[PDB]
Image: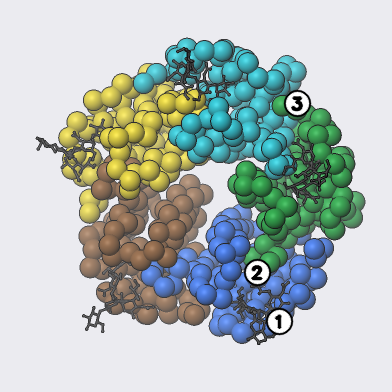
Chain colours: A blue, B brown, C yellow, D cyan, E green
């Protein structure tokens, strides 16, 4: 298994590490049908999503998708600095694969 | 996928953006049969619901409805300022589709 | 849909509004078989339960029962003032149908 | 339904009330197979478990077991004083049936 | 049942106690397919994982794996000092079996 977010991110195609080093500026959550998703933005202007669950996801990802949304909300609310995001860059906005935080 | 709440809200009919820019004044939660719902009010006087799950909801929305209720409670309790709500205006009170918070 | 706890509470029989305006004094939680329930008391001496799930509950209430117990715990722990409780008065102690909090 | 932890505890065999009146000293959580359990200790030296789910549990207890572990963690982390524990004394360490907290 | 993390850890093969006595330095969470996992590091330079769920896990562990990831996040966020980790040493990085915290 990978030992860092960067190492994990390299195990995939169409991914890149964004070094954020900042707390989340805005949190957006939708329960509208077909748009069950979370959107986060930063001071940098960069916007990121957790995608709507769909056929691009395998079973093992369903709970992890829910976990990521849980993490984004509590990260937002505690003003916790996110270190890095591993994101897929074939989606608009870029889609969150992994998150890291340092303290 | 949409990049902001406003953009997401535009992908639906009978929706409008309320710019709230305030913490939640009151939180009401019900486990009474056929009224399994949350109601939030603001200082502005405006009241909003998360609807009882029903036939107007698709399967993908069940977990998101529960998420929205989770978010409203923790938002309330932390006195977090809500920025915008995307709501359906063909329900009374208006029904929450999406929420945003800025920091 | 109702716009306030009081309005919601009036849609049912054997219910009444208790104006609490206080934080929870004691929180009791049981995982003993047939007594999977939460009990709360106040400084006023009044005691309230979330009933054990049973045949008086419809399916849509299962998740809401669990939510109400979640809310009672976090409310207790944060010393959050409860405003009102809608309770069923044909149970001993009185059984929680809805809760409100103002800030 | 019972109105206090003590009253609830008396509806069972092999149970006793421990008056703790203290915050949790240590929290131990295991995800090892056949040892999916939580252990808590106190300054008094007394140790308590939430048992591994097994055939001694009825269906209605599955969620309540998970709730009890949730409560123990958040209680530990907030340094919340536990008042009383209703425990089964036919297990080693004694097994948690109910918990109460006063404020 | 075991009464301490050390005692529990001894009921398994390929395990060892790491005495950490420190808060978590970094928290990494991934929802990428086949890498649904959490990684934590410490100031000591030691890295640990909660493994991706797979055939090495029995059914009773599914909920416990999710709980462990919940605990790591909230532990990280509250800067709570971990005391000990029971870890499997036949995985890279070492894989978390149990955790303890003292206060
Ligand atoms: C790049 C891509 O299409 N990914 C989609 C994936 O396709 C699989 C293979 O992609 C990789 C990858 O994601 O980069 C290759 C990695 O080595 C794998 N990494 C690890 C650590 O296992 C991952 C991983 O297995 C999956 O992501 C987990 O589900 O997959 C890709 O190389 C392979 O391509 C085949 C192709 O299918 C076939 O038509 C052609 O004949 O040959 C190609 C070259 O071999 O296909 C793999 C699956 O068959 O498939 C998943 C569903 O399994 C998704 O569709 C994924 O798309 C991304 O999904 C993300 C969410 O998980 C997110 O939405 C991204 O935006 C999507 O692009
Ligand atoms: C307006 C309406 O009745 N919406 C109900 C919806 O109906 C479907 C179509 O809905 C839209 C919409 O809701 O605005 C159109 C959007 O482009 C869609 N957006 C996206 C991003 O896909 C949404 C979305 O797919 C759904 O909301 C997700 O469930 O749907 C609606 O336009 C369509 O109307 C047809 C009509 O049926 C047909 O006779 C006629 O010839 O063509 C019309 C369009 O040209 O019907 C669609 C259903 O097949 O359906 C959902 C559940 O399926 C809801 O019932 C929705 O009502 C709202 O539900 C909300 C909660 O999700 C909330 O309760 C609101 O108050 C409800 O009005
Ligand atoms: C009062 C009562 O007995 N409630 C039980 C309920 O019975 C149903 C009807 O009750 C009402 C009510 O609770 O006030 C009537 C309301 O208008 C309804 N309000 C709304 C917004 O929907 C509610 C609501 O539907 C339910 O609470 C949700 O399940 O129900 C009751 O009037 C009706 O009695 C009829 C009977 O059906 C008929 O055959 C007889 O001959 O005459 C009566 C009078 O016309 O029966 C309804 C059910 O068929 O049913 C639910 C289960 O669905 C429960 O059993 C409920 O008991 C309460 O449950 C609470 C928690 O949910 C709590 O434990 C209380 O202590 C219980 O009394
Ligand atoms: C004491 C005991 O062995 N309990 C096990 C239980 O057995 C049932 C009866 O237990 C009581 C009890 O716990 O004291 C009696 C109480 O009045 C009941 N209280 C309420 C509110 O219902 C409880 C309760 O029903 C259950 O605990 C909920 O699951 O049960 C016990 O009296 C009865 O014993 C019979 C025996 O079966 C029969 O052969 C003999 O002829 O007469 C005896 C006296 O009537 O059996 C009852 C069920 O068959 O069953 C549960 C699960 O079904 C557990 O096995 C329980 O063991 C405890 O489980 C705890 C966790 O829930 C914990 O791990 C303890 O360490 C276990 O002892
Ligand atoms: C060492 C190993 O490979 N363990 C895998 C396990 O194998 C079972 C036995 O493992 C023990 C153990 O892990 O120490 C023995 C303990 O006494 C048990 N402890 C308790 C408290 O009950 C545990 C426990 O029951 C399991 O973890 C339950 O999930 O298991 C192992 O001794 C036994 O090996 C046999 C072999 O099968 C047989 O061919 C040969 O003739 O004799 C051997 C030695 O007597 O096999 C047992 C299974 O039948 O199986 C589990 C899944 O059931 C895992 O695969 C486990 O591998 C580890 O899994 C961990 C996560 O759970 C982690 O990822 C580690 O990295 C894996 O090594």
Front residue of B30 and D1: D1
Spatial CA span between label 1 and label 2 = 12 Å
Q: x%, y% of residue A73?
A: 56, 59
Q: Is residue B2 above or below residue A57?
A: below
Tell me what residue is drawn at x 25 percent, y 48 percent: B34
Q: Tag 3's secondary structure?
A: loop
Q: Is residue D76 left or right of residue A73?
A: right
Q: For the residue carrying disc 1, how many other residues have a C-alpha within 10 Å: few (<14), some (14-19), or many (20+)?
A: few
Q: x%, y% of residue C79?
A: 50, 34
* Callout 1: CB less than 8 Å from ligand 1: yes
Residue denoted by label 2: E33
Question: Can residue C45 be seen from the camera position used here?
Answer: yes
* Callout 2: CB less than 8 Å from ligand 1: yes
Q: Is residue D73 left or right of residue C97?
A: right
Q: x%, y% of residue E51?
A: 74, 55
Tell me what residue is drawn at x 73 percent, y 60 percent: E28
Labels 3 and 2 share a subunit: yes
Spatial CA span between label 3 and label 2 = 37 Å
Question: Where's ligand 1: which quadrant?
Answer: bottom right
Subunit that carries the residue with mark 2: E
Q: Tag 1's secondary structure?
A: loop
Residue denoted by label 3: E3
Tell me what residue is drawn at x 67 percent, y 33 percent: D38
Subunit that carries the residue with mark 1: A
Residue denoted by label 1: A13
Q: Are marks 1 and 2 in contact (CB under 8 Å)?
A: no
Front residue of A70 and E64: E64
Upstream in the sequence, badge 3 or badge 2? 3
Number of residue marks: 3
């Amino acid at each position: 298994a990978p030992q860092t977010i960067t190492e994990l991110c390299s195990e995939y195609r169409n991914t890149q590490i964004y070094t954020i080093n900042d707390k989340i500026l805005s949190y957006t959550e939708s329960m509208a049908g077909k748009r069950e998703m979370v959107i986060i933005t930063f001071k940098s202007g960069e916007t990121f999503q957790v995608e709507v669950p769909g056929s691009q996801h395998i079973d093992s990802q369903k709970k992890a998708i829910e976990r990521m949304k849980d993490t984004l909300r509590i990260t937002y609310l505690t003003e916790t600095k996110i270190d890095k995001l591993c994101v897929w860059n074939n989606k608009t906005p870029n889609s969150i694969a992994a998150i890291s935080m340092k303290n």
